[PDB]
Length: 298
Ligand SMILES: CNC(=O)c1cc(Oc2ccc(NC(=O)Nc3ccc(Cl)c(C(F)(F)F)c3)cc2)ccn1
Image 1 (cartoon, rainbow, N blue to C red):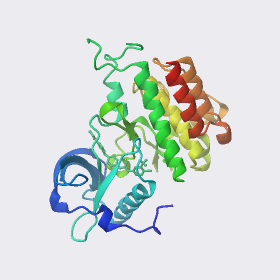
Image 2 (cartoon, rainbow, N blue to C red):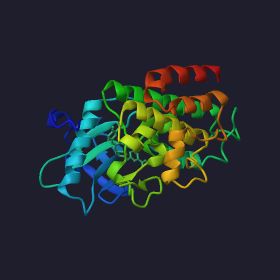
Image 3 (cartoon, helix red, strand yellow):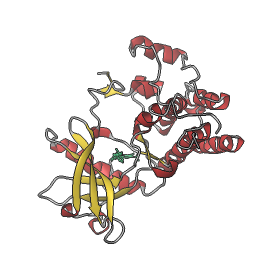
């Protein structure tokens, strides 16, 4: 499951630490961090490139180092896709810290970004040049579904799909990622204490109750991600304490109301992703086809 059998090809991925100029932090948890860096010649010969470097911080143990190595292997296993954050290289040599180097995405995470554009949105479109529109939102949804369809094809599951784990790069390209240990999950209100600190508002009933993670529970989370996108970055389940009674109502069939910027069809898609039976939710392949059609109709 963590790719401990498949090897690391150093000649392909290894990047020298002394060609990496580390800069300002991009995100910090308790044990992990992401740092902005300039990398000389990491992918194009003798060309300086801005990159994002995931690494441990002081306080990390070897257990987190093992987790970071497994993350490097998972990214190598998954391979390249436009809508998955692109692995560029790694620093794995002894005598320095493990570093996982990925592409830098200009606009950061999608939640924060959308939350800043409420005053820069029109449903259908020079004064409006940098505005989001309904087309951008369906387009972002489409791209995340394509990315997840790809992940499913590599026999992977995300386990933490949410707008905070989507990056927005140039030209309206979104990329799925996992900040993981580079997010302070104690101080982040999206992760609630259960037994573990877990993203309960994004989790399917079977995951909350039976600790079952499959690609179909990722579909549930994708539905919540849609809600985040068509609320322009609102926090899910507004006005609700996330306690025992929330978990019961969810099981009983309670669901979020339509968000402010949704279409009727998009809301029905959120409801489809939140079907109580995992097998009756759409697949990511069906989500791709469906969102592609909605993009046409738009
Ligand atoms: C302003 N710009 C930034 O702040 C910024 C910050 C970045 O920080 C990041 C750096 C590295 C990562 N690492 C992953 O994502 N690891 C990963 C592990 C398992 C799995 Cl399954 C996946 C997958 F496949 F889901 F994608 C991805 C995540 C975010 C990157 C770009 N830009």
